[PDB]
Image (tube, rainbow, N blue to C red):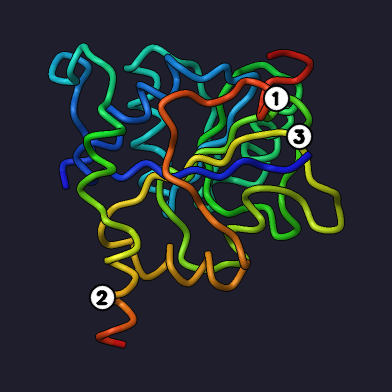
């Protein structure tokens, strides 16, 4: 959870919004929340 | 007219990199960036300045006279970005602001509502971009349900007509 990370180590390329969105299956996660409620 | 709402999925460790990409790819006129604490507002404003972008910051642990002077300077456009906590009890609506970023996703639906507009007003052009981590899942679910809204995954290209006044 390292909030602070300098521009030197920040990757030169743009953040991969698309690849990271695949790590959160919103509909399945919401169904998991409803199942353990 | 109405605010277009998106979310980007991140870990705490990736938020700054994600924020850097938003600054370089969004046609921001003015922006407001919300955090969940006074300490995080200070840390983030220092970080945005190291990224190379101008910003003012306000939070609850500041002297009244300083907070008011900073807000009035931002409203006058002395800077393009403002980092802050939930200080607007009736909400916020400065005209040049076309982009709101929830660096930290709020806990309450009324807090979320106050960040993306002011009480007793119609909808206006703009974007609301939410940085979501796995720990925000319950709050994301409940705020969408309470408001009766859909916070869509951030697309590959954001149509400029959704947030750029008189352009594309």
The residue shown at (74%, 31%) is: B72
**Residue receiving disc 3:** B94
Task: Tell which subunit mark 2 falls on.
Answer: A
Badge 2 local density, few (<14 within 10 Å), some, or many (20+)? few
**Mark 1 or mark 2, which is nearer to you?**
2
Q: Which mark is residue A17?
A: none
Quadrant of residue B46 within the rendered picture: top left
Residue A8 appears at what percent x and percent y? 15, 14
Taking A7 as reference, is B163 left or right?
Answer: right
Q: Earlier in the sequence, mark 3 or mark 1?
A: 1
Residue B141 appears at what percent x and percent y? 43, 68
The residue shown at (60%, 60%) is: B149
Residue A18 or residue B67, whichever sits in front: A18
- Cβ atoms under marks 3 and 1 closer than 8 Å: no
**Mark 3 or mark 1, which is nearer to you?**
3
Q: Quadrant of the C terminus of chain A?
A: bottom left
Q: Is residue A9 above or below residue B125?
A: above
Task: Tell which subunit mark 3 falls on.
Answer: B
Badge 1 local density, few (<14 within 10 Å), some, or many (20+)? few
**Mark 2 or mark 3, which is nearer to you?**
2
**Residue receiving disc 2:** A32
The residue shown at (72%, 48%) is: B117
Q: Secondary structure at mark 1?
A: helix
Asked if both marks, 2 and 3, belong to the same chain, the answer given is no
Q: Secondary structure at mark 3?
A: loop
**Residue receiving disc 1:** B73
Taking B107 as reference, is B127 left or right?
Answer: right
Q: Secondary structure at mark 2?
A: helix
């Amino acid at each position: 959870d390292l909030f602070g990370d300098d521009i030197e180590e920040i990757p030169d390329t743009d953040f991969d919004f698309e690849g990271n969105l695949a790590l959160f299956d919103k509909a399945a996660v919401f169904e998991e929340i409803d199942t353990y409620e | 007219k109405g605010v277009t709402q998106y979310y980007a999925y991140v870990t705490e460790r990736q938020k700054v990199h994600c924020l850097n990409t938003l600054f370089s790819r969004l046609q921001i006129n003015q922006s407001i960036i919300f955090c969940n604490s006074s300490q995080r507002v200070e840390l983030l404003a220092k970080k945005i300045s190291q990224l190379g972008y101008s910003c003012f910051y306000i939070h609850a642990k500041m002297r009244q006279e300083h907070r008011n002077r900073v807000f009035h300077d931002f409203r006058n456009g002395l800077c393009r970005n403002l980092v802050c906590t939930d200080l607007f009890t009736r909400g916020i609506d400065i005209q040049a602001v076309n982009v709101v970023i929830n660096f930290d996703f709020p806990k309450l639906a009324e807090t979320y509502l106050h960040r993306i507009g002011r009480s007793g007003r119609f909808g206006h052009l703009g974007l609301a971009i939410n940085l979501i981590t796995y720990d925000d899942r319950f709050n994301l679910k409940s705020i969408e349900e309470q408001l009766g809204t859909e916070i869509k995954p951030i697309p590959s290209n954001i149509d400029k007509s959704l947030y750029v006044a008189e352009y594309h």
